[PDB]
Amino acid sequence: ASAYQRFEPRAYLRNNYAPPRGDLCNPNGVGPWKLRCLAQTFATGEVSGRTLIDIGSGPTVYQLLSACSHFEDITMTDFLEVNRQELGRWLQEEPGAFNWSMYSQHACLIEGKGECWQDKERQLRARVKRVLPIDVHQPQPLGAGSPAPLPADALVSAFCLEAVSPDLASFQRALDHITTLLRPGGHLLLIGALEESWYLAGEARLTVVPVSEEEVREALVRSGYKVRDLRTYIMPAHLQTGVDDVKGVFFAWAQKV
Amino acid sequence: PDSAPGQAAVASAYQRFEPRAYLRNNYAPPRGDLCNPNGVGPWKLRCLAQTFATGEVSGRTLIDIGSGPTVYQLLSACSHFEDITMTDFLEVNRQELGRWLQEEPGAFNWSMYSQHACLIEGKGECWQDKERQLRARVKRVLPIDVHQPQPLGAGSPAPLPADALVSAFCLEAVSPDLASFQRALDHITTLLRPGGHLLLIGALEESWYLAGEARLTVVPVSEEEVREALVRSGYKVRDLRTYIMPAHLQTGVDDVKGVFFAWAQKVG
Ligand SMILES: Nc1ncnc2c1ncn2[C@@H]1O[C@H](CSCC[C@H](N)C(=O)O)[C@@H](O)[C@H]1O
Ligand SMILES: Nc1ncnc2c1ncn2[C@@H]1O[C@H](CSCC[C@H](N)C(=O)O)[C@@H](O)[C@H]1O
Ligand SMILES: O=C(O)c1ccc[nH]c1=O
Ligand SMILES: O=C(O)c1ccc[nH]c1=O
Image (cartoon, rainbow over all chains, first blue to last red; front, top):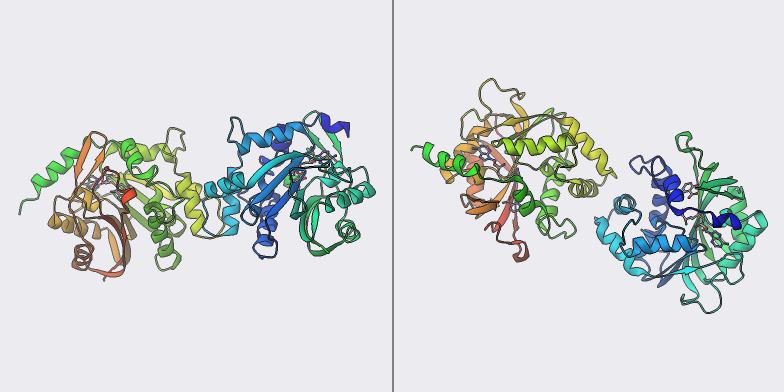
């Protein structure tokens, strides 16, 4: 856990959201794949409501681009101060903010409603009301009297749980911990790494639990979800880059039942 | 009768045309605000994209007539032609294009326009690929005078006759009157093969516009004047659509009342 104390936001963004993993031009890469999963799911019309929470956002916003037009109250979270600070920089268009414009643009491309990427960002920034501390290990991940409208209509989380969990069972408990924040009938969009065991964030070396698709599936069941969709992306060689050892990325669409 | 004087005034005036001021006046916001779908920027891009989307405008060679310092008019086009000639009267415009071709940072930034063309062509192309394709396909930037019967000069470099022509806001902006306009249209029509296509965009009912110190003269034309000249030149008009300049886009940079888009195919 203390390992996340060395976690460098910029190095993380560099390793994961700049080229080659950050090149959105090629349809076969992980970035486009994730954006595609998110967009397709929301285009169904079946994930809707007023409030949404993003569990373990880190310094990233890409995972809400398609989401932001189906929820007017959005809550972002992370365990580290530095990540929340980094988010603020983008939300407030402050100086030195990370540049997400390529991703906004591509979400506008994929969604295909003729939306300009500035409108897209504008809405996102508008609908994110708060950026809050959170610890999934706690049965009440958001603490007692959070300003977060509970329970949420929907949840999103990407590359968080498996990355904060020593083993399968901690991963299971965490899933249970965040699930409490989710209204019955609500939706969870879980994105994460397949069979990963470590990744680097500057001086920080983080341990990861290597999970399989079927493992992810069963965990969702055991947490009280009906799995609407589970797809896998296999990591091409050219995107195996020495920053981690992830083999693939899973996308899960689940519904609390 | 004698075309020389008017043409001379025209050439004279254009010696004060300042590319940056023009780029600013016409392609920076609000006119350059690609976010408003009711805006002229988007309407122009739509007209081009939809037209190329028919698959009916095709071939090897394309010539853009009076390109000025702008490339937006070629964004949807460049996927449909291997060889594209760009052209302008003024060296300073030609140099501007050079700066963009070289991908210099001093260049005007067209990427909003690129992204927007990518958006409405609906093929999920990224804007960097679109721009790289345009830079690859532009084979040359030539001097041009549409008042000369051979607008490119004799023994020109351009592969003639072209398969297609593009021209935006050029013919009316350099012709003192309708007869001049028509002649200019006749001239460029010689560079196009029979059955070839001409995509024409221009100002409706404009008489002047600004480009720095330069306050330049435009022949005001109407849609029907434009239609007749096309027929008069040997074209079948496939499409002629009009955009009315909204008040908030009428900024004192010109007096254009609207914009026309013509898809025409040369008879022969
Ligand atoms: N105990 C804990 N509870 C909830 N989040 C935690 C946590 N310990 C670390 N995190 C956060 O989990 C994130 C893993 S990586 C960030 C992933 C980001 N959502 C994106 O999609 O790329 C980090 O931001 C990290 O600080
Ligand atoms: N006699 C002539 N023959 C051909 N082009 C001319 C000309 N005199 C001026 N031009 C060019 O006509 C242009 C009008 S401005 C339009 C530029 C660009 N195509 C656009 O769409 O914004 C200027 O570039 C100008 O230099
Ligand atoms: O953030 C990550 O760990 C990640 C994002 C996308 C693909 N693969 C990853 O490991
Ligand atoms: O005159 C122009 O250059 C012009 C008028 C209206 C819309 N767009 C233009 O470029």
